[PDB]
Image (cartoon, rainbow over all chains, first blue to last red; front, side, top):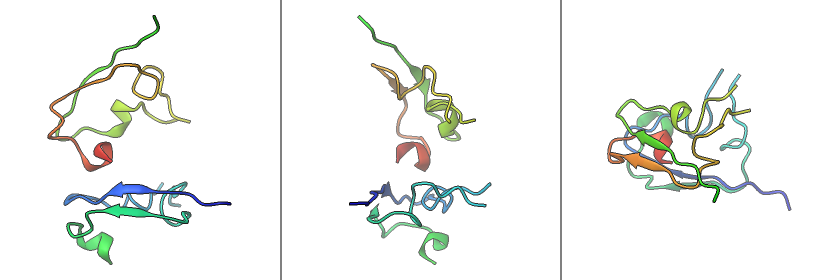
Length: 52
Length: 52
């Protein structure tokens, strides 16, 4: 009944401020911490900060 | 009868605030969300936030 989708493509130069939300304390309105179903395309090419 | 154009050149340091309009909630007056035909030159060099 209440589910929010999230489509994102992981790149080689992707930053955590564009997946979970940029900070100002972090503007995470509609991203990953408040999403029922998340989609991450091409996960075998992300950075070390997003993997941790 | 009612169509708006949009010409923009994607650079290596382009930000989504200059393509989809800057935020204040987002000043999208004549940019991409309200445009019938959009033109993006050199799309093979944009950032990860604009491509997603």
